[PDB]
Length: 87
RNA sequence: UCUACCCAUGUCCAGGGUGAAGUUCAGGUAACACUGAAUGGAGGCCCGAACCCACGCACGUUGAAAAGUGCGGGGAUGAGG
Ligand SMILES: [Mg+2]
Ligand SMILES: [Mg+2]
Ligand SMILES: [Mg+2]
Image (cartoon, rainbow, N blue to C red; front, side, top):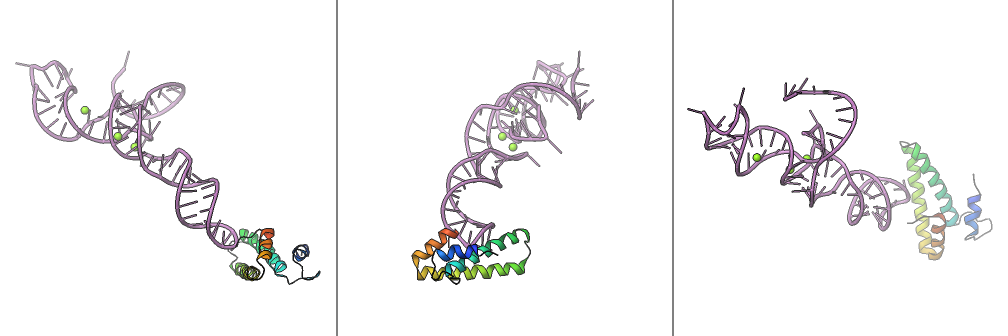
């Protein structure tokens, strides 16, 4: 467990001090879980059930990224640079 | 001392072509795949002298020669000479 990743990408674009539901925070946590799960699948190549989990996370993260991009174009660009995404 | 195979140690193979893997960059996707370009220089790879071979024909047949010559021919970085 890491609230580290919360308090980092809360404060970058914080609505509240104890913001949790910011797209920033969500996308960041998704990015952390995605990347963790990828390295599981490097080892456990034929864990297909878990891999469907990955594809759902990826789809959530994409949809939240498309949401920012349409909402706040600058705020989107700051998030993808810090996480190191492309889209 | 010919020749067959082997062992040790040397050496030879003008030139030209083709463009494997890999790599890089770009694209590419959540990751990979995958795509393009450049690079790269593989091969009992290609064309072709030396060299090695001996497919066809002619000639020769008391020969220039007890196996050759002429004109073409095959291999030519290899299980090579
Ligand atoms: Mg050859
Ligand atoms: Mg040749
Ligand atoms: Mg000849």
